[PDB]
Image: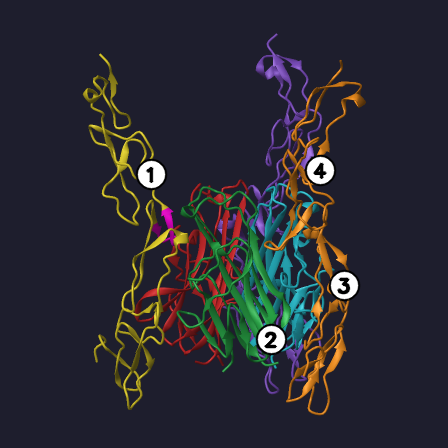
Chain colours: A red, B green, C cyan, D orange, E yellow, F purple
Amino acid sequence: AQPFAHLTINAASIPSGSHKVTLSSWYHDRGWAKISNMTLSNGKLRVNQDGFYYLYANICFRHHETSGSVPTDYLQLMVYVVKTSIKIPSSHNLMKGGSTKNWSGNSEFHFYSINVGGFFKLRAGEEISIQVSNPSLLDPDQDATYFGAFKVQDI
Amino acid sequence: AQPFAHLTINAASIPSGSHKVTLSSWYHDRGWAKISNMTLSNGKLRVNQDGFYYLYANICFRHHETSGSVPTDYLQLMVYVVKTSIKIPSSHNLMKGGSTKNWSGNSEFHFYSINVGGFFKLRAGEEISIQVSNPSLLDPDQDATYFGAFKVQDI
Amino acid sequence: AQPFAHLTINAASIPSGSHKVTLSSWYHDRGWAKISNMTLSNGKLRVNQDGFYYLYANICFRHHETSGSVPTDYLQLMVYVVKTSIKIPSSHNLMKGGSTKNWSGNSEFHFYSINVGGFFKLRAGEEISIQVSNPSLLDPDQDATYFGAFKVQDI
Amino acid sequence: CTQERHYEHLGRCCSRCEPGKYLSSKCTPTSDSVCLPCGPDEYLDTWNEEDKCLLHKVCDAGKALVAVDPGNHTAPRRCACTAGYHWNSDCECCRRNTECAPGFGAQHPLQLNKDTVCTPCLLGFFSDVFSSTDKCKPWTNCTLLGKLEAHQGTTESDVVCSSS
Amino acid sequence: CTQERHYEHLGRCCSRCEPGKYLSSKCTPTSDSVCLPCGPDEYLDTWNEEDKCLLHKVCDAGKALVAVDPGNHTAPRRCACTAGYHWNSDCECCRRNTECAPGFGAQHPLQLNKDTVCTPCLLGFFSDVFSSTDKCKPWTNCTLLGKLEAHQGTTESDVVCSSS
Amino acid sequence: CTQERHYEHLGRCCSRCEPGKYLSSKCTPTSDSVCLPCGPDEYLDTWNEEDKCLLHKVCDAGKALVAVDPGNHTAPRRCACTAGYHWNSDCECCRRNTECAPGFGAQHPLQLNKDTVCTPCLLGFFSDVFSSTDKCKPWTNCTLLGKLEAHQGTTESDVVCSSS
């Protein structure tokens, strides 16, 4: 029936920087990852059928001692759900979530998750994508990092 | 078809206190803000048609150095999704989210977001509204602070 | 019509440990708690009809001085949304959320909430349940701790 | 038609439900409202048109809250913060009562679930401590110690007594 | 057919909407695109096929942001971080400008909404402080103090002057 | 009919799928279950009725986790916390192994992915440090240093040797 998608992070292709990036690899056909009447190119979820969809994302950040010290500096773990036209320049923010964090403590492990969800009017050709602040901090688990959409009503 | 609403904070009318307040100004017709078969008076989203709706809210709190020092005291950033009858006294909580925070550090910027969502049975005449603890800390962005609803099933 | 459920924590039966546990008592017929064409046994929400459901959970953790000191040690407040077959051994994680926290400060009160939501393919006989890390820290309020589901589409 | 028991549906002036019960069925053109009693731990305290009763507040010990009035099908459960705390509506939590500084004392009697209000110590009394419970103590009488008053007292300190 | 004003719908080469307005209705086989003007605080700055205009950025004072260009129905609102800060795209926030350490000074003129770039002090100048605004100061001229140069200066310290 | 290969559908005793594959189609009245093999990085390790195979655990280096058994279409991938850590099911994370205090030592051999268990040093041995790896050291033999034993040792300290 209606279009939908539940994309889980491609555990094998997460960028390694500390700078904000658009995630460009998600699974769409394994585990809980699934897609229907929607297109996934490179981190871009293309709407193939006009309508009002509920869009959501769960992002998990994690750090472990063995990976090295957490430098004493500015830490803001963010997720931005972005909308772009498959043929119209700059993307725009639909949803934003996150938190400034201090992970300098002497604990072995640090963990943090963000969730965002909203009802949006989408057109075929429009694309939904995910941006995160610290990619190397991303948790690769399918139950941890993912985004999706499902149509709830026609335009 | 079904009723729905995605209300984004009216960036120009956020109260300035530190005390809990019911937000009374949201956009309903600009940017991502939209409403259909639902009524918005003053922060109160009135249900115009019985049914089971999914209700959600994303609230972003932020503080910057230039705004002054963050007093060393109790900081609990909360959001309460409240239900009230357009003709029945005290409101009741549907959903609650938030976190106690310490923003005394020497960092220039502090940021934090909360999200809540649930499935509820609503009647025409019932109103949904948002309460937050520290209004002057609210992020005015449309992708940051908002709430909505969409009907998924008849009663 | 479609199946659904909004389960609120059974304020009178929350386990008291500090170890991860599957919550086994929710209300299904009082306040905002409701269920339809779905079965709730002991913390296990059984799907009675194949389909794609949106699953969600809001978990609130809280601590007050009068309850004693918060030991200086590892604090990770987590929620795991788990799927199990009413006749197939080990459960698997669908969704994960949470945060490492330090609640050693001298503040009277500590509070923290997590939310998770996703679109999943479920079969009659499959069960959805909730696991949390620190049960004695759970907020008993109906607007604070709960999980639910609603069918949005047939298989 | 009045509200203290009525509302309007299918052109009819239907009867509103009484505290202790909710409307199971709106009035039809042939019958009136069907009002059923509130279930366990539920209540409605006004003439209503609710399809479900309100659930009672949990007086969570974990929030330093205790039941002052258990409530029932007609009245809501009332809670209070335990000793040393008072309910704060901004945090919806039990906040530690504020301390009176030296020179002031807690006004008595101490109100349950309310913050302590401080007032300065008046002539003949003092407080040399930070407390949210103590009121100003009266100066020591040196003769009870078998002594004379070496030094007068203040609002912040007690008199000084010395063996003559 | 070209894009600088056209797009394709029902087999027809329909006209694209001009900045300042969005398409209210896609072209039918009998009529062309119906483009209506952007509402208050909205804008579209390109020939488009949008069913709604873009909402203007909020230049939140609370983020130390200020409007450099108010924007309008044709152009987007432009914001800048106020003095002492520069916009950081990773945090999408106004970050404190970095400080130049002793021996270096801030390159001038200071760019609005950009981070300060440091450069070492060259012969005859010094900086003995951590600052994100100050450039290297020239050494003191002892004769203006009515003195002689006791000690030569460095990049980190000023000359030392002594009354002869 | 048995389960080690069967289940019930349309009144029929249909065959269950074998590890390595999932059921693509439930049995119809005319044919039996259609079981297809698990795709890449997937597995099912039991006779099942699953419409999709289970995805393998990620042995995230970022969690100090490493693959002990890569797993395959029939067996799940097994992970272990790297040296110095052990898996904790409450946090579902690799926790730092606990340290044995002076007077005790780590029991050997050290179990992979398990916490270190401490035991007190017995006569002739000591440990004067906090370590999650070291076992009790035996007392020094003074004659190897060309000395005599000035002081006996304890569980917390080594013997004291002195040149005669």
F73 vs C150, nearest the viewer: C150
Residue D99's spot in the image, x, y percent?
64, 40
Residue A71's spot in the image, x, y percent?
44, 42
**Alpha-carbon neighbours of circle 1 within 10 Å: few (<14), some, or many (≥20)?**
some
**Alpha-carbon neighbours of circle 4 within 10 Å: few (<14), some, or many (≥20)?**
many
Between disc 2 and disc 4, the foreground one is 4
Quadrant in the picture for residue B144: bottom left
Magenta residues span E87-95
Task: Identify whether E78 is placed above or below D151.
Answer: below
Give the amino acid at mark 1: Glu
Mark 4 or 3, nearer chain start: 3
Task: Identify whether F143 is placed above or below E30.
Answer: above
What residue is disc 4 on? D135
User: Label 2: chain?
Assistant: B
Taking the view exactly as shown, the residue that stands out farthest to the top is F164
**Alpha-carbon neighbours of circle 3 within 10 Å: few (<14), some, or many (≥20)?**
some
Per the rendering, the mark at residue E99 is 1
Same-subunit check for callouts 4 and 1: no
Give the amino acid at mark 3: Gly
Give the amino acid at mark 4: Lys
Question: Image check: C5 left or right of E152?
Answer: right
Same-subunit check for callouts 2 and 3: no
Q: Residue at position x 70%, y 35% from top?
A: D136
User: Label 1: chain?
Assistant: E
Residue C43's spot in the image, x, y percent?
69, 65
A13 vs F136, nearest the viewer: A13
Q: Residue at position x 60%, y 58% from top?
A: C79
At mark 3, the secondary structure is loop
Task: Identify whether D144 is placed above or below B118.
Answer: above
**Alpha-carbon neighbours of circle 2 within 10 Å: few (<14), some, or many (≥20)?**
many
Per the rendering, the mark at residue E43 is none
